[PDB]
Image (cartoon, coloured by chain):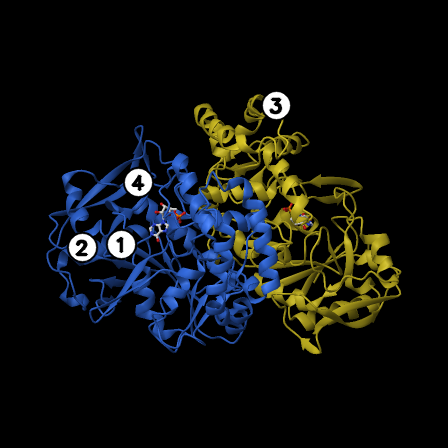
Chain colours: A yellow, B blue
Amino acid sequence: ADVVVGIQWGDEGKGKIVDRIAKDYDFVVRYQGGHNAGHTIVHKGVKHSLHLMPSGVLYPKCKNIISSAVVVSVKDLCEEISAFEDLENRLFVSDRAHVILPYHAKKDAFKEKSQNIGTTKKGIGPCYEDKMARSGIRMGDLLDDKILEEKLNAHFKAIEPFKKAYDLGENYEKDLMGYFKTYAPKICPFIKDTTSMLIEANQKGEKILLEGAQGTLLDIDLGTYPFVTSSNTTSASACVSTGLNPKAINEVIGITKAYSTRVGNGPFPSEDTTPMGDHLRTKGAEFGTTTKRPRRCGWLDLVALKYACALNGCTQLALMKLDVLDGIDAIKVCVAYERKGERLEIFPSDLKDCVPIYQTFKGWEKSVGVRKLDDLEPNVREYIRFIEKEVGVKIRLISTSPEREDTIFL
Amino acid sequence: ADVVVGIQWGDEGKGKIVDRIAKDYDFVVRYQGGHNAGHTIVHKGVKHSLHLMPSGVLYPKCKNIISSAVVVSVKDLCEEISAFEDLENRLFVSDRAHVILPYHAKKDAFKEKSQNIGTTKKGIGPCYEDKMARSGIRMGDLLDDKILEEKLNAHFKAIEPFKKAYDLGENYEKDLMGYFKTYAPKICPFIKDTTSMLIEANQKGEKILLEGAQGTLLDIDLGTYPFVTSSNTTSASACVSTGLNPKAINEVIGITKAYSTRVGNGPFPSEDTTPMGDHLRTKGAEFGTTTKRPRRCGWLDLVALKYACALNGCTQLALMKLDVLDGIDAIKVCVAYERKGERLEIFPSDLKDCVPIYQTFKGWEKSVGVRKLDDLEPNVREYIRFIEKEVGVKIRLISTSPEREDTIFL
Ligand SMILES: O=c1[nH]cnc2c1ncn2[C@@H]1O[C@H](COP(=O)(O)O)[C@@H](O)[C@H]1O
Ligand SMILES: O=c1[nH]cnc2c1ncn2[C@@H]1O[C@H](COP(=O)(O)O)[C@@H](O)[C@H]1O
C-alpha cells in the first residue's frame, strides 16, 4: 500500500496528487478526519470540491474507501454522493466509522469561545470525543432501526444537561430522528466492512493508495498541540485503522507546498507578516476556493519538514503550487531556528521563542503550467535541488498549477 | 524497531515476554494506554507488578520510554518509580503524554452507570476524551508553573457544571493544586522530548522494543466496540505516536494465551461457561495477581487470532500460559463461526449470533516449567503445530510458567 500524506499543516495539495496517480490503484482510501478537509481537483477547467469523498472518484474503475477512523457527517456525504454517477460498487463507507451529530458542531462552536483553537467548527473534535467516550454512534448502527433508535435515545438522555449551554433547539430530538429518517436510506447501501475488504486486497496484492487529510503538523499526538486536529494524520495512522499493518506500507509521498500556510491559530515559526510575505498572501492565502478562511502565509520550514519526513518515513516528496511563487522577487527558506542564542537543527516539542533562520533564493517568473523538467527556469530547479538535499528525500513530483496534468514526474 | 503486541483482549503475557527479551534492546517503549495495564514480571520467586512502568525496568542498561500516546496518572507513576533504584537516565516520560486528573476517574465511574462497559474505572477514557477536546493537560505543562496554573484554572472553570454530577469534592480545586505541588517536583526530572529521542535512535540503528498494552481486540477503532479501550493497541499505533514511521517496524511478536480471557463486558464467541471451562476458571480466571477482577474464560479463537495477526502484521507468535492447561482433560479451539447456518472463516464487524465451531484436542499433564522443546509432551507440540498451521504464523516463543526463564525459543 502507498500513502499520500501532507507534511505541513494541511492544504499542501494532497487531493491533486491522489487524483493524478489514482489511475494506477485499485483502492483509494480516506483514512481519517472528516469534512473539515476541503480541497479541489481540477481537470480541463472543471473544478471538483471534495470534502470526505476520496480523490479517486474521477476514475470509475477505482474503489473509493472511507475507512474506520473517519468521522462522517452523513448529510454532507450524501450531498457529495449526489454529484457523481453510479457510485454504488465504487464507494464504500466503513461500518466502524463514527457519525457526526449536529450537537457536535454546536459543542465545537461553544468550546471555541474559550479555547480559540480556530477549528473548522464542523464538530470533528467532539465526534472523536464521543468515540473515546465509547458513546459515539457508528455507521453500522444505521443498518438496524432498533439499534439506531436505542443509541439515539441514549444520546438524547446524555445530552439533556447541555441543551441550554450548546443552544440546542427545542426540537433537537424530533429533528435528529427525522434527519436519520431522511439520510439513513440514502447512505446505507454504501456501508460495508471495509476492514475485511482491505485485509483481503492486501493479501491478494491489489494496489492500495491511502489518502491523508489535514497534515503532519496537525497530528493530535505529535503536531503543534493544542492547535491540531483530533485525529492522527501520519502514514502510520493509515495502517492503524484501515486493517493494513505497518509492514504493508511501501511508498510514502510527502506533499509539501513550496511555501507554508496554516489556517487557524497556533505557532508558525516561518510565518512572514512583512512585505516579503505579501506576494504569498495575494496568490496563496485564498487556497483556490472550497476553503473559506484565508490562510496565514510563510516560508518553507525545513526543520519542520525533516521532522514530518521522519514521522512518516517519506520515500518521495511532491513539491506543490510552484506557480504561486511566479513573479516573486525572492524566496526564503527557514533552515534552522534560533532560540535565545542557540541554533536548533531539530524540531522541538515547544516552539516558544523559536525564531526562523533564513536562506534566501532567487525567485522565478513563469513556472505555471510547465510540464517538463527541461522547460523550468534554472531558479526553479535550484530551489528543488536545495530542498531535496537538505531534507534527504528526493522530490519526485512537481506541480505547476491546480490542473491534474500540470505535473512533472522525475 | 520490534513490537510486542497482545493479539487477544489483553492479559496475554506481554510483560513477561518484554522482560524476557528486553536485554537485547537499547529502548523499551510503552506507547499507549495507562495504568489500566497491570501485569507481573516474575524472576527467581520475586514478582514485580507493573502498571505504566515499561517492562525493561529490570535491565538497568535499558532506557525505558513512556511515549506520547500514553495517559499518565502522575501519582501512580511516582509510586512505581519509588520501587526501583537510580531510574534517572533510564526512564523518560514524553512531554506530550496526557495527564489523568482525578475528575477523569470520577467521570469514568459516572458514565459506567449507564454504559456498563466494564472499564478499569481509572479515568483512561475521559483522559483521552480531553485529549480529543484539546483541553487536556500534557506532561510538558508540569515543567512551567505558570503554564500549569493557567491550564488548571481553565480546567476548574470548565469542570464547574459537573461537580455535583461527578461527585467532585468541595475542595477539588485546592486538592488538585496540592496534588501537583506534591508530585510535579517528583516527576519533572523524567519529562523529555521522547519523540526526538526515538527518531534519533532509529536513525542511528539502535535497538528499539515497543511494548503494547491491552490487546488488539480492545482497539478503539477495530476491536469489539464499545467494549474496547480508548486507545489504538496494534503495531501501527506503536509508530503513530512514538516518532517512528511504519517502515521502521521489523519483528512483530503477537502474544496469545493458549486459551482466551476477557475482563469486563462485551462479546466473546469462544467463552465457555460449561463445566468444560471450569478448569480454565480455577487456574486462569485469577490472572496471577495485580489484576483484581476475575476474567471471563474461554477457548483459543482462531477466527479472531487471524484477524489480529492481519491487523498487526505478526511475524512470530508467543504462546503463553501453557501450564494453566496442565491436567485439563480436553482443549477446544474455535476454528470458525456459525451464524444462522452460515460458516464464517473471517472475523466480522458484528459478532451477533456468531456461535463458535470447535475442534477438540487432547490435553496434557505437565508442561509447567519445561524449558526445552524436547521435554514437552507430544500433546503440547501437536497443539502448537495446529495453531501455527491454521494461523500461518510460526510460534517462536512458548511460556510454561510466569517465571522469566520458563520460556522456550524456537
Ligand atoms: O483540511 C484542512 N486544511 C487546513 N487546516 C485544517 C484542515 N482541517 C482541519 N484543519 C485545522 O486543524 C485545526 C483543528 O480543526 P478541526 O479539524 O476542525 O478540529 C484547525 O487549525 C483547523 O483549521
Ligand atoms: O490491561 C488490561 N487487561 C485486560 N483488559 C483491559 C486492560 N486494560 C483495559 N482493559 C479492558 O478494556 C476495556 C476498557 O477499560 P479502560 O481501558 O479502563 O477504559 C474494559 O473491558 C477493560 O477491562
Chain designation of label 4: B
- Above or below, A408 relative to B285: below
Marks 4 and 2, how far apart in space? Answer: 20 Å
**Image check: A147 left or right of A351?**
left
Q: Which residue is label 4 attached to?
A: B268
- Above or below, A303 relative to B178: below
Chain designation of label 3: A
Numbered disc 4: secondary structure: loop
Residue A399, quarter of the rendered image: bottom right
Residue A42, quarter of the rendered image: top right
Q: Which residue is label 2 attached to?
A: B324
Residue A409, position in %: x, y?
Answer: 70, 59
Residue kind at label 3, given as amino acid type: Glu
Residue kind at label 1, given as amino acid type: Lys
Same chain for the residues under marks 4 and 1 in the image: yes
Please say if the residues under marks 4 and 2 sit with CB atoms less than 8 Å apart.
no
Tag on residue A170?
A: 3
Q: Which of A226 and B269 is in front in this view?
A: A226
Tag on residue B257?
A: 1
Which of the marked residues, 1 or 2, is nearer the chain's N terminus?
1
